[PDB]
Amino acid sequence: RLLCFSIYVTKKPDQSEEDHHNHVSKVNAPMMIPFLKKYGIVRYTVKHNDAYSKPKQAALMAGQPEENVLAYDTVFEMIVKDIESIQTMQKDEEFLRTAIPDLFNFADMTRTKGSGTWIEEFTF
Amino acid sequence: NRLLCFSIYVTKKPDQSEEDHHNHVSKVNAPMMIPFLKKYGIVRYTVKHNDAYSKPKQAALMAGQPEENVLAYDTVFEMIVKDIESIQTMQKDEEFLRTAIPDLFNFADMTRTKGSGTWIEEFTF
């Protein structure tokens, strides 16, 4: 059974949505990727809710009341075989001085939410 | 060329056991869904379970977080597609309307479903 760690990010207050998502894709992702590789993350997914995706979300959610649109600026998902992979990553000396301070440059750190699940996956 | 993701956040049917909910989802709903997902070109389908098996792992990951920060639904479905017309056509397929749609009422609280639509980046190692 594979597990999934989901991180639901509200963008830094005052930060443009364009600045937020550019930082996430162009700076945070290449910062993250070496740690994810080193600690055996199977899959990493970054989900963006911005001007580009919003009309598609509005079409998919047509006929739903707005409070049914569970919308965060960015959602990260890490799929792993064991949560110890993630906990060891997060305490990695280098992680604490790179990925952790970078959070304050794109996330409202008073509002983050998360979940841990077991998953089934299908590809075609 | 950006992939899109449709996320469906499901609260279990009132009075349904966690065990019954997740067995129905994995064993009945998934094989019901898989042919439609294939036919309509969904790239990836992910079913995320929050039950007795995952809960101590989530408690460990979320250690030190206030309970209201644990955004927890019973089941989360994610469909990754090249464009949303794939999904909308699937959902209006007459066979979908008499199989997948009624099956929702046998495992989901249909007054409480939430969703989102996002564009995604994906990495494998």
Image (cartoon, coloured by chain):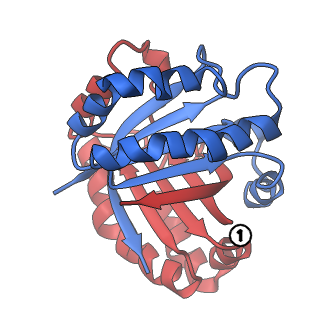
Chain colours: A red, B blue
Give the residue drawn at x 79%, y 26%.
B16
Position of the N terminus of chain B by quadrant: bottom left
Chain assignment, label 1: A
Total marks placed? 1
Residue A13 point in image, percent of width and height: 42, 40
Give the residue drawn at x 81%, y 40%.
B19
Residue, disc 1: A83
Q: Is residue A105 left or right of residue B15?
A: left
Q: Secondary structure at mark 1?
A: helix
Q: Is residue A70 left or right of residue B27?
A: left
Residue B105 point in image, percent of width and height: 61, 20
Quadrant for residue B17, please give it.
top right
Residue A26 point in image, percent of width and height: 28, 67
The residue nearer to you, when weighing B118 against B105, is: B105
Give the residue drawn at x 46%, y 30%.
B115
Residue A93 point in image, percent of width and height: 63, 84
| Above or below, B74 relative to A25 | above
Position of the C terminus of chain B by quadrant: bottom left
Q: Amino acid at mark 1?
A: Ile
